Length: 122
Length: 371
Ligand SMILES: O=c1[nH]cnc2c1ncn2[C@@H]1O[C@H](CO)[C@@H](O)[C@H]1O
Image (cartoon, rainbow over all chains, first blue to last red; front, top):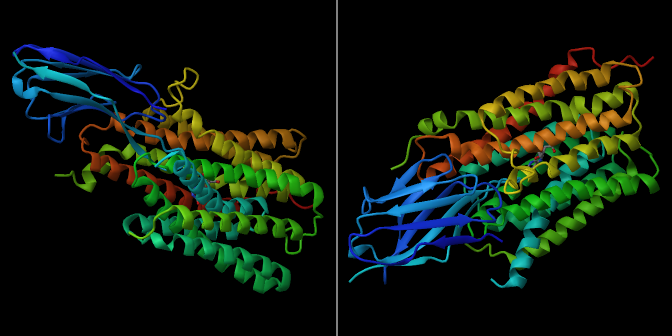
């Protein structure tokens, strides 16, 4: 099986920062992208950041200029340093890994992590 | 989707792949005339490339499989009760339509598997490989207990057994398909995507173009014609390809293991790695035009085709696993799916150009004279 392990959830005062770390274990085949999708309480999942195998970074304009995504390929670990926090960023963050195998035919598979709760208040 | 349904569906996809590729595998195993293999490959690539851009309904999969089964029955009937010219005509037309039908069925199965959670394409790939190795094993078990009658250059009882096995496995696949599956119902320009991943498309064409130049043609059909290779040894030589072609697809995918870390390396290094594959062309020709015992050896001919098969499968999967790493301006999900479609087209174009390039070697006096 494929296991996505995350760390970094918690409660932070406004204006603070966090670091979200995600690691992939099985990933049968290659691994094309690793990203973070945040889901607010009572809303749908939305992209926050994405990091390719090569190094291309995608961002959501809500967090543009605040969150910085860093990657690794030997360990397939993705880090997200999230800065200048404000209350509207509270959500549950899901680590997503998009892969590809092509043993005899091309297959695209996405693995989603459990998700870490991130709260900004007080 | 509990464990029972998941197991049933995975088995169904494995059976789909195995039944689809059993016809090609038994055509290779029976030492069928080369033009029939060429026709089958032509039909397969044409149908696959056409069906990539056309969403054919997924209710036609059992019908296509049944058509393949009745075509195998027609093979048996024509071999048993037809003359030379009738058998040849039926073989050519049936192999063309078999290529077309198999391509359409594989496209339908790929579409059905991909458009699901926990995508099932890997199971169909495993089914294809199991088809290859299973046909190999069946050929070896048959060669012990079957007389070599060779009615029209093809063994009689061996053909009958292979095609009844193909029909049986295909009907079982039909039953599984009916029982399990539900068959009821800004972006960058294409030129921009092609300019990014032009190496990946090129590398996919090169590997398939070279390996179909040699294997079914110069590969085991000009060594046998020249050195009078025994029919028992041919199945071993052909088998070394089908066994090692499957087993070489896997190590590139299992890069999380320390052993297979370097199996997916690059695209620039892949281009020069396909150039070293060009050294196979002198090797295959020497096996057919040199007489001293080293080249008239079953051991090195098996190795000469195991190496071709291993590099063929290895270098077919590598461009898929690295093409996303080198591209620059493709970032959406749809674009990468489009690019992956370009790569599979390069595969089928490679198969078509490779199989028809074998006729270039007919000009050269490669094979030894009969005396
Ligand atoms: O129906 C097919 N689907 C996918 N690949 C095929 C098919 N038929 C032949 N080949 C390809 O021919 C080469 C020599 O065996 C193999 O690479 C095989 O993938």
